[PDB]
Length: 41
Image 1 (cartoon, rainbow, N blue to C red):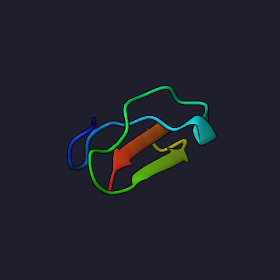
Image 2: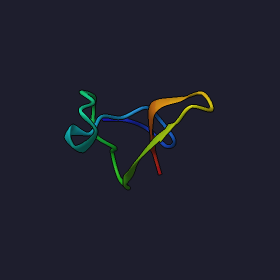
Image 3: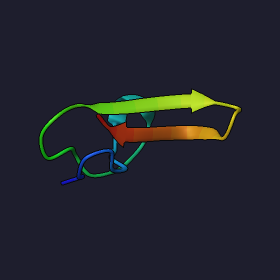
Protein backbone atom coordinates (compact mmCIF):
# COMPACT_ATOMS: atom_id res chain seq x y z
CA UNK A 1 0.00 0.00 0.00
CA UNK A 2 1.00 3.64 -0.48
CA UNK A 3 2.64 5.50 2.41
CA UNK A 4 1.92 8.96 3.82
CA UNK A 5 1.67 11.48 0.98
CA UNK A 6 2.73 8.69 -1.37
CA UNK A 7 1.60 8.19 -4.97
CA UNK A 8 -1.52 6.02 -5.05
CA UNK A 9 -4.09 4.95 -7.64
CA UNK A 10 -7.76 5.71 -8.24
CA UNK A 11 -10.16 4.19 -10.76
CA UNK A 12 -12.29 7.33 -10.49
CA UNK A 13 -9.38 9.12 -12.16
CA UNK A 14 -8.53 6.37 -14.63
CA UNK A 15 -5.30 5.92 -12.68
CA UNK A 16 -3.99 2.44 -11.87
CA UNK A 17 -2.03 2.39 -8.62
CA UNK A 18 -1.76 1.05 -5.06
CA UNK A 19 -4.09 2.07 -2.25
CA UNK A 20 -3.25 4.17 0.80
CA UNK A 21 -2.30 2.10 3.84
CA UNK A 22 -4.47 4.20 6.16
CA UNK A 23 -6.12 7.45 5.09
CA UNK A 24 -7.57 8.82 1.87
CA UNK A 25 -6.19 9.35 -1.64
CA UNK A 26 -6.27 12.85 -3.12
CA UNK A 27 -6.28 13.07 -6.92
CA UNK A 28 -5.45 16.43 -8.50
CA UNK A 29 -5.47 17.75 -12.06
CA UNK A 30 -4.14 21.10 -13.29
CA UNK A 31 -1.98 22.39 -16.16
CA UNK A 32 0.34 23.70 -13.44
CA UNK A 33 2.39 20.50 -13.39
CA UNK A 34 -0.60 18.45 -12.28
CA UNK A 35 -0.94 15.47 -14.61
CA UNK A 36 -3.36 13.53 -12.41
CA UNK A 37 -1.35 13.79 -9.19
CA UNK A 38 -2.89 11.41 -6.66
CA UNK A 39 -1.20 11.69 -3.26
CA UNK A 40 -2.15 9.84 -0.07
CA UNK A 41 -3.68 12.34 2.36
